[PDB]
Image (cartoon, coloured by chain):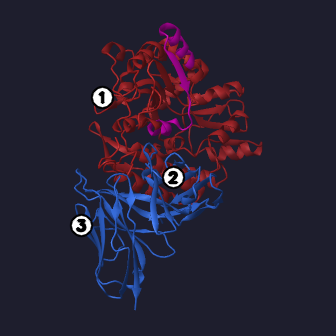
Chain colours: A blue, B red
Amino acid sequence: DIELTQSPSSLAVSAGERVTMNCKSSQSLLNSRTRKNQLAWYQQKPGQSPELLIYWASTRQSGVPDRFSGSGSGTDFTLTISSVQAEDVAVYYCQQSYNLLTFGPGTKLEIKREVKLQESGGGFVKPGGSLRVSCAASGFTFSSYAMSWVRLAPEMRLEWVATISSAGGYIFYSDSVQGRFTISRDNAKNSLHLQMGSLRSGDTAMYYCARQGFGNYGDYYAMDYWGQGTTVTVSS
Amino acid sequence: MKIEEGKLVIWINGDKGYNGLAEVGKKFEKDTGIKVTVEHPDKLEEKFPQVAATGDGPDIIFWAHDRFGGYAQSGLLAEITPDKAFQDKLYPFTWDAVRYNGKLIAYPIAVEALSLIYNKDLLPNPPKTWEEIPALDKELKAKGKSALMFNLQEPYFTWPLIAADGGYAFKYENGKYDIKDVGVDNAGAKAGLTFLVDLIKNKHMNADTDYSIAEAAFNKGETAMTINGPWAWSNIDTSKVNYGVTVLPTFKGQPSKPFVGVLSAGINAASPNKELAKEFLENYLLTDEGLEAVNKDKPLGAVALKSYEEELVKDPRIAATMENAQKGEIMPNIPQMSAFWYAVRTAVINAASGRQTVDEALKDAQTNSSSLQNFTLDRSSVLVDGYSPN
């Protein structure tokens, strides 16, 4: 119900240039209670899972170099790299968390001169078939965290699929998969699952399990650790 | 999202006497026409808050009181309304266990504590102390038996040894739990758990041991002692091992200190039958005949209802339960107990399995139990139109 645009869709810079990336939403993302803006920023470097950069619009995640900088208010958000570097070649995603979860379409940026999560269980299926992806968690109190499934589809398409609360009472699915998919967890075996049935060929993607982060100041409403994507191909 | 009016659906654990409870149900039906359905979902202690969050689930939920603070803060529980007259039928300390923010949130049923259960034929004089068990196993190994086998996968069973010498969960000071005073790290805790691990290192126990391994071990007469609650008695009864129930061994001269659980009945907040539930609980279950129907299926042990406890406590096994109960501490029900259990469960399993030292395992459990500012229980990490669900 919330749409996000990111401009520009791609971008080529020489090393050292200062870079600003836009994100605009169909509506205000401000949390009337925490006064935080429900927007987060992610970096997906080629061959890797996305990582958390910014959450609450302007708060940098631990470990993120300070040349990365998030700003913005209302419906208008910006990620700035003050002086870009070689290691920053990546697609950058804004993600809203004001009403469920939506990833923006992404900005491809090119340069010209013990918390562990392991997925398993992807594969091929005919259209209308089934598969159950899993994700084994270690290095943290899994019982205490909400977990989410996010998938990456061939055309730079990062999509939220489902989220399940730390104790399982609260579950939410993307429209794209509602009814057909079922997210479950087993807090006893430290495990998360996505049963995928009535598969469309558009469901072909790398599927990531991701931990929803929180801390002493409140929920991040962002995913701070990701597994490597298990792959699901629906081939006619 | 619909519980269905004009019907009672009850959830209770599988080791308790659900068929007995179901016949209290049928009595309720012929008197009032209301159908009563008893189910025993697996892991119902987690199934309940999971389905009740969106307003589904049973009308009545049974568990030890410890989890009920947690359910109540999550709003999954109705405030119960027994008048003073019914309240007096039950022991006052059991009502204290069903309080949360001054409010009564469940009906107490039974008072549970682990006892030492021994094979009388293999071992006529059971050990007063934990210390003499290693040598008692060597003897018993000579005749192809072991001395002790109990559940190590559930910290509930290992807690009595940990607390014997001063291990504690949260400190209870001036009428309140202080969730920044955690004792899973102290010297008493370490002394107990080290002793349990040494038991495993010296081939007297297996880290491997779980409930059903230890049960069959005892009921097949292969181990001289087990540690269990009154629920376990009926399987021991049918097996006809000649068994006794008695005081838990001392550790370092101190009694083992089981966490006492008050088995309780909660009414779902989302239930449309809250009056029918009150009536069933007050007028049918919590009667001498009510509790006996359940008890004859699977023993409840000691019960919160005075009139029936006075009958039950005549049984030396219930006397033992009470004695052990009196030497332990009533569990807290504060929401953080969930975090704690997970924490200690991990510590006990990792220390016992070797993957961690006792000092490392308990330090972790203490970290994971301490700074729980506003521990949540069911963290959704999602907003819906800018607001959290529930």
**Label 3, label 1: how far apart the Cα atoms are:** 46 Å
- Quadrant for the N terminus of chain B, please: top left
Question: Magenta span has B82?
Answer: no
Q: How far across and how far down the image is residue A45, in percent?
A: 45, 75
Magenta stretch, main secondary structure, is helix
Q: Characterize the local packing of mark 2: few (<14), some (14-19) or many (20 or more) Cα atoms within 10 angstroms.
A: many
Per the image, the residue denoted by label 3 is A72
| Rendered view: B28 above or below A79 | above
| Rendered view: A12 above or below A102 | below
* Residue B130: mark in rendering: none
Q: Characterize the local packing of mark 1: few (<14), some (14-19) or many (20 or more) Cα atoms within 10 angstroms.
A: some
* Chain identity of mark 3: A
Q: Residue placed farthest to the right in the image?
A: B143
**Residue B255 seen anywhere in this rendered image of the structure:** no
**Who is closer to the viewer here, A81 or B375?**
A81
Q: Is residue B148 left or right of residue B275?
A: right
Give the structural element (helix, strand or loop) at label 3.
strand
The residue positioned 72% from the left and 42% from the top of the image is B140
Question: Magenta span has B42?
Answer: yes
Q: Name the kind of residue labelled 3 in the image.
A: Gly
Q: Nearer the viewer, mark 1 or mark 2?
A: 1
| Rendered view: A159 above or below A175 | below
Per the image, the residue denoted by label 2 is B346
- Stretch in magenta: B22-50
Give the structural element (helix, strand or loop) at label 1.
strand
Per the image, the residue denoted by label 1 is B103
Q: Residue placed farthest to the front in the image?
A: A236
* Chain identity of mark 1: B
Q: Nearer the viewer, mark 3 or mark 2?
A: 3
Mark 3–mark 1 contact, CB under 8 Å? no
**Label 3, label 2: how far apart the Cα atoms are:** 43 Å
